[PDB]
Amino acid sequence: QGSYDYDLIVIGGGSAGLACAKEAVLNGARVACLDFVKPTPTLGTKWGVGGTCVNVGCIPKKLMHQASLLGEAVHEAAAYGWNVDDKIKPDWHKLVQSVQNHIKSVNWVTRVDLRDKKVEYINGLGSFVDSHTLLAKLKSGERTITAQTFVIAVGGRPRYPDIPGAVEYGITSDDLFSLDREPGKTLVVGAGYIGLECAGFLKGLGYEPTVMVRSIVLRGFDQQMAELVAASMEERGIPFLRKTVPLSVEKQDDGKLLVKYKNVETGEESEDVYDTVLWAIGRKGLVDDLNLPNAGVTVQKDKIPVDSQEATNVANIYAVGDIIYGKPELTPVAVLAGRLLARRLYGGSTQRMDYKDVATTVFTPLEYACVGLSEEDAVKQFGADEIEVFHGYYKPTEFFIPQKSVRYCYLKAVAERHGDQRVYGLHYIGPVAGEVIQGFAAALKSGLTINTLINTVGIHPTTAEEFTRLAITKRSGLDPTP
Amino acid sequence: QGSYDYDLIVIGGGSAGLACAKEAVLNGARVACLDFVKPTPTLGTKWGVGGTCVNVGCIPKKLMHQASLLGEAVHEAAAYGWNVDDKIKPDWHKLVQSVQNHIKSVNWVTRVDLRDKKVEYINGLGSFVDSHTLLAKLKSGERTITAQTFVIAVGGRPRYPDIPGAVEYGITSDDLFSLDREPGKTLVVGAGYIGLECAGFLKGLGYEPTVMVRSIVLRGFDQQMAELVAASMEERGIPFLRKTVPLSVEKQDDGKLLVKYKNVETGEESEDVYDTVLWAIGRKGLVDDLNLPNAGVTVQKDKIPVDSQEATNVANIYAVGDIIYGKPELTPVAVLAGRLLARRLYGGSTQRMDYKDVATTVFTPLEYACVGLSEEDAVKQFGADEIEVFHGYYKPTEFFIPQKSVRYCYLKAVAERHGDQRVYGLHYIGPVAGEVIQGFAAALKSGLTINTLINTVGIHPTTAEEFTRLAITKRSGLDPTP
Ligand SMILES: Cc1cc2nc3c(=O)[nH]c(=O)nc-3n(C[C@H](O)[C@H](O)[C@H](O)COP(=O)(O)OP(=O)(O)OC[C@H]3O[C@@H](n4cnc5c(N)ncnc54)[C@H](O)[C@@H]3O)c2cc1C
Ligand SMILES: Cc1cc2nc3c(=O)[nH]c(=O)nc-3n(C[C@H](O)[C@H](O)[C@H](O)COP(=O)(O)OP(=O)(O)OC[C@H]3O[C@@H](n4cnc5c(N)ncnc54)[C@H](O)[C@@H]3O)c2cc1C
């Protein structure tokens, strides 16, 4: 009660913003949704509607990971009697065209879907004038629009190190999936899931990545599982530069990139030449252009703190997805929080988003999926002596004939030691990690216990059945290799 | 412990028998385990210890399915820009050799493990003298041993139709996996999972199968899903002879096999020529050679009815696995039941086998996995108006670039309509169906409801997350294709 141009304005058109805008209209709101994509500096990469996942995230990364797995499949096929040739090579440019052809088909479908659902899509950059007023800057011109409620869904963009040559000579994941030039010998700075997945499918597509790690691999993940993923990448011939930080990048006369770098423990300074330098050193939330102080919204560095209803400290302004402080930065999380948020606003729902036990997958050459607590978090939370860890190495049926290493085929269930022996966390390295873990995440939400887990009849022959076969505890001290 | 040569004699060295034998010795019993493999009649195929799964079942079937899938991966790789050659053909002799090579390694490790664990392995055919005495026929002489307790775990062997030429010219799954000659053009008589799987990998390896179906496809399975499986195989060039039954087989001068057959609906008589006739029309329990009347054990046709502790009507004699009457005939069922039985006999356990909601996968070219009730059984049991079926067609991310048909990529959830909305059944046709369904099967055993299902965050991008995206009910009559 007051009267504005819209019930709801959503700022940002990626996973959360669009899910939110669509669910809001379904429930009868009058809604606008702004989306705009700043081109990468140098290179100037830009793209269509639908945000990070579709354009420069989950989707192209999965497709290139598939490109890399298919190469290996071609190699294994010979072991099974197929008369395949060995000297096979990927055309990078055909790969990139395929992937970009897919993404642009998706951009169109999404654009049509919005218009069909009557979501008013504005292609401009929104900034607050006040807690109820937004200026949209359009390709040419501006509109000032009001709303009862604002959902901030602006996400982030890749960070650049504060080092000479960084922006002129390096790229990020924004550039990588449409790179005009072949990656070639590549330096991947950062050992979060993005850097690892990148290095992984670079090696698999015939290039030469090296991963540079400042301190640890996959911070926020179970560190045993982390180190197993890193060693499995080294087994695949991907070198790692541990405890090492970039100093500078310069272009040589021959067009090669000379990177000087520094070991952070020893102080040792080194250099090497690469064709490509990929920064995968984190993503910074896009609060900057919002002019949040005009709106009264408090900020926590580059992110926005929200209550369990995704409200900011300003009662009418909400934020959802990646710009939000301290929550899983993942697509299905953005989508579902976006939608639920529209449903409480307009569909009379009280269902709040559940952020606990979110499953995830790192799509490394051998993939790592997990849901729930890491081993160390459970131990910190409850005490070593109130925790049980069941573990083992296993052998995929599909690995024997081609003789593929099973050295890093390992899984573990982290659980309550007594009582109901509640399962806290599940971790798996191996083929189709995410396909395996998804149903187990649903089980953890239904209260999975160790007794149920271990008495769920296996589907044979699968690697998923290895979770139901778990029996050796770390406490027993018994060899986890059957 | 007192009077007999053994605490325990296990008759049958397959999935149930070995799991029973091993667990029994772990709990201090003195055990022998008999295994003997009768050679196939004609042809005379025979193999080592470990039973059907290892030698003529799950394992070779999974390996040849993998060979067929790798063939498809090779063709897909090109869509992603790999410069692979199109004209590839598998070598059957090389494939059989790699499969048999794996199975002989496993036979030997299994034998070694039995000795290491002190299970006394006797390669001889057991028949009862009385309820405490067994005669063992060895290659050499005969033994005659006594025990306090017997576990019958003899399983089954494929059936032959009672039809001229059947045994002289036909083969079964027992011969297939080490066929000396190339299948060629093959009539697969029977449309259970064994027939369909064999037909599927044979087509995938360059041969020309035809499936002959007496009545229905996949009797015992959700029939909607059965028809989608059949049609996905017709999509791949595999024909079905519907409502059709074999009459005879003869060998022509040119070495081919003339099959006379009859449509049982129209009465039509037809014939055709094949290189191979695979009978996949069921398996008969091996009660015959046991001389059960000597033990006083009651049988139910070819099977043995047992109570919920796997006991026969003779209290010192149990049966477990495929020979048992009326239970799922699958490897992990046999393994877990034989384990739990030994653990109750000797381990002071009271835990009984749970035969309900066992998950299974049909490893057809597009795999069908399921757990819990088919739609028709849920409707039968509860009423249409108490059932909600959530369903959808979906598109695997990996299918886009090579433009693979998504026509049969379909899943559904059969659920309680009101109340807690307990999930009764899950069904999925698509890639890595068994990897997807396994965790969901543990979810079901934990009480998975629709609310849990639909609010478990997806792992993106996966096909497994399609389960958590389910939203369109059959009752709405809305299009299940987004
Ligand atoms: C390489 C990489 C791999 C990933 N892999 C996975 C994975 O496999 N699985 C998974 O779940 N997640 C993955 N993610 C994470 C996932 O893509 C993000 O979690 C998700 O896209 C976040 O959605 P969002 O709506 O918050 O932000 P975004 O999708 O980034 O959308 C925000 C949109 O708003 C625009 N915008 C910003 N400011 C304004 C403004 N002032 N006005 C108008 N528009 C604005 C932005 O330009 C952008 O288009 C990956 C991310 C990266 C980069
Ligand atoms: C082609 C095919 C595909 C299959 N695919 C799958 C699948 O992928 N997944 C799955 O879970 N299951 C699968 N199975 C089913 C699975 O193989 C069986 O359920 C399982 O092997 C049954 O185990 P068992 O111990 O009861 O029998 P077995 O493995 O058959 O029995 C063991 C043995 O007892 C021996 N024996 C019999 N009589 C005597 C006697 N009197 N004295 C001494 N020894 C005797 C037999 O010769 C045999 O070695 C498949 C089966 C077939 C045939």
Image (spheres, coloured by chain):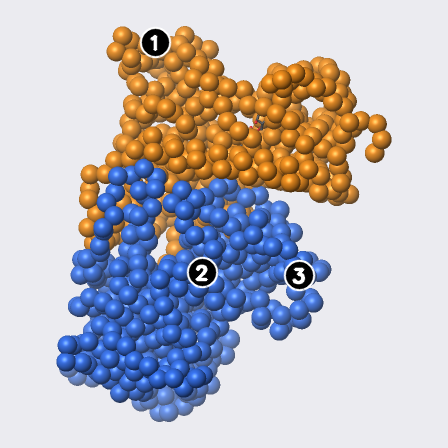
Chain colours: A blue, B orange
Where is mark 3, residue-wise? A475
Q: Percent from the top left, x then y, of residue B117?
A: 66, 40
Mark 1 element type: strand
**Label 3 – label 2 distance at C-alpha:** 24 Å
Estimate how packed mark 3 is, as few (under 14), some (14 to 19) or many (20 or more) residues with alpha carbons within 10 Å: few
Q: Amino acid at mark 3?
A: Arg
The Cα atoms of the two marked residues, 1 and 3, are separated by 64 Å
Chain for mark 2?
A
Give, as a three-letter code, the residue at label 2.
Tyr
The front one of B67 and B394 is B67
CB within 8 Å, label 1 to label 2: no
Numbered disc total: 3
Mark 1 vs 3: CB contact within 8 A: no
Q: Which residue is mark 1?
A: B250
Between B479 and A37, which is closer to the camera in this rendering? A37
**Callout 1: CB less than 8 Å from ligand 2:** no
At which x and y percent is residue A176? 25, 69
Instruction: Using the image, name the chain to which the residue with label 3 belongs.
Output: A
Circle nearer the N terminus (3, 2)? 2
The quadrant where ligand 2 appears is top right
Disc 1 and disc 2 on one polypeptide chain: no
Q: For the residues tagged 1 and 3, is the chain the same?
A: no
Crowd class of label 1 (few under 14; some 14 to 19; many from 20; radius 10 Å): some
Rendered image quadrant of residue A276 = bottom left
- Name the residue at 30% across, 73% down: A187
Rendered residue at 50%/19% (across/down): B39
Name the foreground residue: A394 vs B185. A394
* Front position in the image: B146 or A33: B146
